Amino acid sequence: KEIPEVLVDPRSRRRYVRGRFLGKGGFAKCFEISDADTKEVFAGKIVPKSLLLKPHQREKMSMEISIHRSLAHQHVVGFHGFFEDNDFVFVVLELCRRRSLLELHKRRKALTEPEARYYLRQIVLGCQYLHRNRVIHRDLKLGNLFLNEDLEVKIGDFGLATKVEYDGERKKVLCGTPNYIAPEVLSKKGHSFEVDVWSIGCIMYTLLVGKPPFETSCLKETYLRIKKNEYSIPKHINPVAASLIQKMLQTDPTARPTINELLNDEFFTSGYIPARLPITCLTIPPRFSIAPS
Ligand SMILES: C=C[C@@]1(F)CN(C2CCCC2)c2nc(Nc3ccc(C(=O)NN4CCN(C)CC4)cc3OC)ncc2N(C)C1=O
Ligand SMILES: [Zn+2]
């Protein structure tokens, strides 16, 4: 059951030449795809219906599209359309040519504090937007924070995202395995937006420390630690940073900052936030000199 060389959308009359394989995110296989008219290049997410035999699995795809199609923001992955044939579902997404913060972290490990500020601010801005529109992402991790050509963060993968339908709603269920799973999810006693503030907490730790907050050999031993709040921040981490991590990584959901509180935190306001990063920042730690030589 092989994927077409050209992807034709009969409704919009659009044709996409299937370009080079990018990798296999989940059930989906991802390719650079180019529109035949505009020549505009996109990221195609192609999932075979043979893996969507069950309504439950079909419904998760549908919801992902439902949620992601309704979003437009600078730090959210552009959703440009979807369509299907008898064998596949095709989703046309914003190509993010510098991959994700995961690939950056693999190369650089711990970032400089300004780099963290730069990225975390964009992670927070997109996540503020989701929350404003009642969307919880629920799997914010380095692999889901994509980078465009200018190293701007674009929040992607809405396969666990859920829409809050009514004020004060606690989601009882999360069908999936998020990377930075909040303790209220692991305890299985309800959760809302504060789940995303947890993950951002873990992302900040990881960006600054160079490894995740609760990491172990065993995945269940890690879950043990998240419940128990078993983690510690190295001494070389600056107090203002370490304070904000501690605020975000509280077992109590109600005790964490809201998404609209974060950028007013001392970490952002009393520290240097680059306007932009150079592409060398993918490879080499930037020093942020005041002038060249
Ligand atoms: C459908 C898009 C996708 F679903 C998935 N991702 C990634 C996650 C893993 C699969 C693609 C996106 N990626 C990309 N771009 C790229 C991913 C991987 C490689 C790249 O260099 N790939 N290499 C990996 C090593 N291989 C041996 C060669 C290909 C190169 C990329 O851009 C040129 N843009 C957007 C997305 N988004 C937002 C999505 O939602
Ligand atoms: Zn399920």
Image: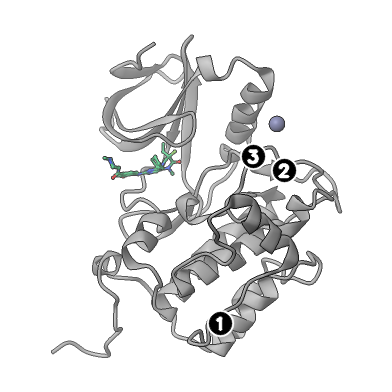
Q: Amino acid at mark 2?
A: Lys
Q: Quadrant of ligand 2?
A: top right
Q: Amino acid at mark 3?
A: Gly
Q: Nearer the viewer, residue 273 or 3?
A: 3
Quadrant position of the C terminus in the picture: bottom left
Q: Nearer the viewer, residue 14 or 168?
A: 168
User: Which residue carries the number 1 mark?
Assistant: 241
Q: Give me the residue at 29% from left, 36% from top.
A: 40
Question: Mark 1 or mark 3, which has the lower sequence index?
Answer: 3
Q: Amino acid at mark 1?
A: Ala
182 horizontally vs 44: left or right: right
Helix, strand or loop for disc 1? helix
185 horizontally vs 219: left or right: right
Q: CA distance from mark 1 to mark 3?
A: 30 Å
Choose mark 2 or mark 1, whichever is in front: 1
Q: Give me the residue at 82% from left, 43% from top.
A: 172
User: Which residue carries the number 3 mark?
Assistant: 176
Helix, strand or loop for disc 2? strand
Within 10 angstroms of label 2, few (less than 14), some, or many (20 or more) residues? some
Residue 266: x and y in percent read: 60, 86
User: Which residue carries the number 2 mark?
Assistant: 163
Residue 138: x and y in percent read: 65, 49
Is the residue marked 1 within 8 Å of ligand 1, measured from its CB?
A: no
Looking at the image, residue 58 lies above or below residue 182: above
Is the residue marked 3 within 8 Å of ligand 2, measured from its CB?
A: yes
Choose mark 1 or mark 3, whichever is in front: 3
**Rendered image quadrant of residue 181:** bottom right
**Rendered image quadrant of residue 260:** bottom right
153 horizontally vs 140: left or right: left
